[PDB]
Image: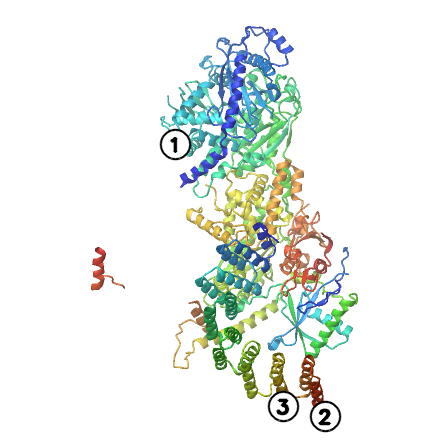
Amino acid sequence: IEDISAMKNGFIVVPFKLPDHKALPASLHFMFAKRHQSSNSNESDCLFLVNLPLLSNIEHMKKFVGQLCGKYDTVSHVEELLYNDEFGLHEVDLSALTSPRNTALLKFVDAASINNCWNALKKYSNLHAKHPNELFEWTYTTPSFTTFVNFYKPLDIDYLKEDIHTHMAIFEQREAQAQEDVQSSIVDEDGFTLVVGKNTKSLNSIRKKILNKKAKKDFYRFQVRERKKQEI
Amino acid sequence: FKSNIFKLQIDELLEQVKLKQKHVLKVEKFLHKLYDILQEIPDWEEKSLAEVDSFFKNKIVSVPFVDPKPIPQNTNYKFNYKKPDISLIGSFALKAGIYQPNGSSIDTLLTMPKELFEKKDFLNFRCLHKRSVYLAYLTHHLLILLKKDKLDSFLQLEYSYFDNDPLLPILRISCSKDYNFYKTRFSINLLIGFPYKVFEPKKLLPNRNCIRILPATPLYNFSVLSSSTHENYLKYLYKTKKQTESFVEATVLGRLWLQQRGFSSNMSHSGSLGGFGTFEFTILMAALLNGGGINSNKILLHGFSSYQLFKGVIKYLATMDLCHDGHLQFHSNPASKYIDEGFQTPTLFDKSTKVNILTKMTVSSYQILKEYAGETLRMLNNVVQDQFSNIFLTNISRFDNLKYDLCYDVQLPLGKYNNLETSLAATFGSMERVKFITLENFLAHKITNVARYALGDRIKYIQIEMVGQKSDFPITKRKVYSNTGGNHFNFDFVRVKLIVNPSECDKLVTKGPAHSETMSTEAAVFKNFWGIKSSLRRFKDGSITHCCVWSTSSSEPIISSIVNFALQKHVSKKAQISNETIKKFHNFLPLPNLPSSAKTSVLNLSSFFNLKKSFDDLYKIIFQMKLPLSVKSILPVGSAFRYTSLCQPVPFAYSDPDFFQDVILEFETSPKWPDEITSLEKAKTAFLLKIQEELSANSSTYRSFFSRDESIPYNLEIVTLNILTPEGYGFKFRVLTERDEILYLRAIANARNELKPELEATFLKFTAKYLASVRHTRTLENISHSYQFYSPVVRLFKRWLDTHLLLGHITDELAELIAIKPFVDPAPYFIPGSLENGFLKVLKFISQWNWKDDPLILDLVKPEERLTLAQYKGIQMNFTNLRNSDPNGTHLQFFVASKNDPSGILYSSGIPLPIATRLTALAKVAVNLLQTHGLNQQTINLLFTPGLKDYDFVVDLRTPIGLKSSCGILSAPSNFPENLNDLSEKMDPTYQLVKYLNLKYKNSLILSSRKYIGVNGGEKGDKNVITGLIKPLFKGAHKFRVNLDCNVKPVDDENVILNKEAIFHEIAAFGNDMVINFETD
Amino acid sequence: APESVADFERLLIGNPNSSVVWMNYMAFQLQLSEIEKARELAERALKTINFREEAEKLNIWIAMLNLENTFGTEETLEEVFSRACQYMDSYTIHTKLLGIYEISEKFDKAAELFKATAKKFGGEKVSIWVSWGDFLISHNEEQEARTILGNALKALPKRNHIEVVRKFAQLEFAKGDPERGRSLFEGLVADAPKRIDLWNVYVDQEVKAKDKKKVEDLFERIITKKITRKQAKFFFNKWLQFEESEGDEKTIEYVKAKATEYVAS
């Protein structure tokens, strides 16, 4: 039960001694990791993290890599963190509609960094598998009533003013450019013009409209012949 | 259509209620053996009083001599018994014997001889004393014959009363486990009566005296004359049963309706309820078959079905008065005629037999029958819903707190029959005995008249139940002997029940007549009725009238005060008055920390109207500010604006979660809105910024800041304007424009097929917050003004849900709808006239609700815009489409709909099936508690204790500061602080904490809390629990994945289960400075 | 094992993502033979499962596909085909319906679906050509298989040409014609004689094909061509493993002698 150190899929368990509770009858926090492969330019040299602890941030991974290099004495320096929808709020871009659950991605600087922290976490897996008491202690930046009144706090009026003004300026620039691009006589390569109207301002919206979208039976002699037939 | 549905439904009820020929043959064989027995009973002659005294002294049977006993110094006649004329009376005799759960009865008349009659036996108890010694001799000889033929092994014989008539005792024989009819559950009654036309009707009239010491005794005249004319009724009903074909189904329908309402054919003038059952229904429908027109037209025809007969007779009892305006006249052996003179008593009169039928019914019984007739006539003329089970399958008479709106327990330590003159304030003399033969009758009529004249218009109807009335006594007793109730009389105490007019439920003064030079008779009865409490006050306009002023109190009503005064004045000095149930209910409602809150009534709205006044001042200011887009509308949409806030709004009380009432601020139409949702919210933020700048630059006394709204998912820039107006109130302005519905529909269109239901939930949250909320608010405010008691009922129901920890996951508008259901549709009950009756009606309805089959359709209106046939059927088709898409209800449980919202999902969306089943289970446990145990302070205390069980863990937390005063409840914060950070400091986080942990462990855990810490944080208002349930999804152990969305622990290299302790330590580190206790299972 | 419908329903409430008991319930209604309740059950499942469970969505997609192949008709196949290609990845739905056609033995209709997926998605994908070659050489139709390779050669880019001739040569060595595989292999080393990984899969496939003289002459051709040190010792030691697995000590000594005169340079 202490030798469950590597899954068949290839995931390394990283247990953690948590700070104990004053009224508790130490404890274990099961963290998982595996390196990620992708042809994306901004998704090179990245580690897939599964079951992150509560509200773990840039500071959390900084303290963790500090403890890791202090223990195993490797050179590994993390760069950023991706896919931190730990709650599930930033899932859908409603803005882009109008105009990796429970996981995270950790960025490193180079292949030396990723391979050094990789063998560090491998030695950590063997560390739990042979002697599960010499592990790290995961700590939270534990919130108190100061962070709670930050969660119940009024907003900064100057920050609000600056954000509103800059967003309005960039939105006006983009809107004016798109309007001119629509009503700037879009002539195709083979002589074809395009039919826009007065008061339209989005060629995207034109494509979106496209994506959204007298039998006189008694006239002739044969027909009146069949009419005579239907009288018979 | 109505014909088809009602015919199939009455066919179902008749095949349900139909009895069996095996039971019929068993009981007729048994009564045939009783026939042989009574023909073997031998006759006997004139004997004397001391002779029959020695007879029944040496014998075990005791004669039931009624009060007063016959005395040989004053009786100059003697006794005899010859062959009685035997007949069988009952529904079986009318060929309508039906199954009854507790049992039924077939009576048998043993008719007394004319040759035994003397022509002056009707005078002065003579014929009834003859009847008593008659029945006693018959009991003795039937006892000999049963000891002879060995039927004594399982037959039990007792004395009883014919429909609770204390002057007319009968016999009652019953069988326990070949002539045994125990499977039939019958009990046969033996009646001693008189033949037809055996005394003078013109001397037997209700105004003709038969007791001399001049006042008459009409009920005694009725008893002797009905016991004479029992069989003429039987042959007349046999004639009408030959004449019409549907009589038996009509009378079983009437009988089941009467027993479902709670009436009976028993005596009601002894402080009981009833007087109208099977026999009265049959005689009445026979008279209505004979006719009933104003010029003797026929109202009911022979070819009518039972539906038509029932509709006709209930139309007659609803429309026509028979007590105070007119009377009905018919002949049994030529036509019936209504005449226009009320006799202040129920008056259906037969001149062929010279009888009044409903003299067992008192005035209050007739009043309640009139109201029930009106209610069922309304439900018959209702064409929209199915009212059938609504009328016939809901016995409301179980709980008196659900049948009547105010119950009153009064104890009467009387003493003795000669101690009456000291223990009463009234007088029970000779002519009082003549008019009101039994002490129970006299005291009951005294309480009815006293309480009715005392209350006046504060009650619609009244009822006096005599708790402890045993209508059964053995053969060895002279009458019903008891020692309960502080005296030797047949009651424990008096239950005074009131059907109350809610508008005049709390009028402070009790207005009387004016003042002339001469003391009028009415003002004289007023002065001798009130004594010290009366006065003569000059009002504001200048009238000079008598009135007895009271004082309002929160904990107890003026009805309680006035009935206390009236009973302790004009009844006795020893009675005890109580309604601690409603006393404790008014105590359980919160009391705001305000001046004069204790003496303030429960219907006061002055705090709400002060809030509205401050809002209107701010409304004028922001309306006359100057903006680039002029303001089009400002709509208050808050819970205080619809009177359903839990804590009443106190000035400067800034810790109640309903401190900031929502207002919608909508500008004029403009074509220059942005067309990108984030920049649109930012433009609305720009408008609010300009508004705030102008306010802080012009009207500096107001204070203001800016907050966020994260209740709408994926729309993260919604900024709201918090405004603190210096009368101590807060409003968060949010802006609604003409582009929001368009952009949300466009987003849900352009989203792909997986994420479409997520944006469905998003748009539905948006609608329920912004658009239908305004309609909801104005509708509920209007109908609350028409229904005052809706606001205390919804406040008590929200308190109940908060203490049972369901409010965090059930929205307040759904709470208000499920609270207002009984006020809108109280069928078949009454409109609630007490906080107690309303809340318990809500609990009974939510317990009996089967939401898997039954949707909730409401028509939020003033009493008699309603949802017509097409809209009703369309909403039901929406419901059945939802149930075909979801038969089990894993996604939706409550389908509630009204005129402002025919969708059916809009308010009950996103509700956990554990929470819904827990709510229904709590209601069922509550109603079973009230079924097994009587309603009292311990039961309601157990109702309000939180559960804390069935939860897999509980987390007990406390705040560093008690919040009762800051929430505004006395057992006060004067001014706003100079720092909004200190406002956030005195604020409370626990709801945001439990919401964020719900959002975190939404895949695996259900975490609930208490919302209102100011009432539910103990005596200081500083405690909050966090209960947590594990899903079966992670109670099972599963394969390792990548989007499992839980903190886990593997059981091997492939399969994993959840990490309970790690969750617990995460919550502990989150609430490190706040969590105190933690219990696990 | 659960048997009753109420227990089935309560387990579907208890686990909404357990596609294994979802297919147990659809198997139960197939044993009781209700295709109407089958399609409504698939509709209820696609309504109740999560949106981020795309693997379970694909599983219920192929589930309704299996039920409409075994017990449905061709018009329903077209309807669910269209709705699945509208919702999920149409090339994947093409391959799954292809595989169900393989296990249901409809040769001509499976072949029409090969033509369909080759005309729509043959410009960028290669696995449809792999599966078409597998079907046609299980049908033993070699010249039409070669013309399908030619359609891949004219419809794909150059690196995809290399991949399709490589996979066709591998399936030729596996179950097709070995001399045709040899011909495409020598043609491929005539186009590109440098590709060490290509030479590696070539020598692994001949040492699994077990033809001794060709193993010899191909390895001598590797001796004649330029090879670096690590790949040289790789080919040398794997040839040692082949010769010791078959047991020719004279060839063992020959390889050790040529290895000594190679390292003595």
Q: What residue sits right under mark 3 in the picture?
A: C225
Q: Nearer the viewer, residue B593 or C180?
A: C180
Which amino acid lies under the numbered mark 1 shown in the image of this protein?
Phe
- Identify residue for label 1: B304
User: Where does residue C100 sit, x and y in percent of width and height?
Assistant: 51, 66
**Contact between labelled residues 3 and 2, with CB atoms less than 8 Å apart:** no
Q: Nearer the viewer, mark 1 or mark 3?
A: 3
- For label 1, the SS is loop
**Discs 2 and 3 carry the same chain letter:** yes
User: Badge 1: how crowded within 10 Å, few (<14), some, or many (20+)?
Assistant: some
Disc 2 designates what residue?
C264
Between B147 and B915, the residue placed more toward the observer is: B147
Disc with the residue nearer the chain's start (2 vs 3): 3
Residue C44 coordinates in the image, percent (x, y): 52, 57
Write down the quadrant of residue B765 in the picture.
Answer: bottom right
Q: CA distance from mark 2 to mark 3?
A: 17 Å
Three-letter amino acid code at disc 3? Lys
Q: Which mark is residue B121?
A: none
- Label 2 with label 1: CB-CB less than 8 Å: no
Q: Is residue A148 left or right of residue B402?
A: right
**Residue type at numbered disc 2:** Ala
Chain of the residue displaying label 1: B
Describe residue B556's horizontal placement relative to residue C115 as left or right: right
Q: As rendered, which of B922 and B377 lies closer to the eye?
A: B922
- Closer-to-camera residue (A96/B657): A96
The answer to whether one can see residue B538 in this image is no
Give the structural element (helix, strand or loop) at label 2: loop
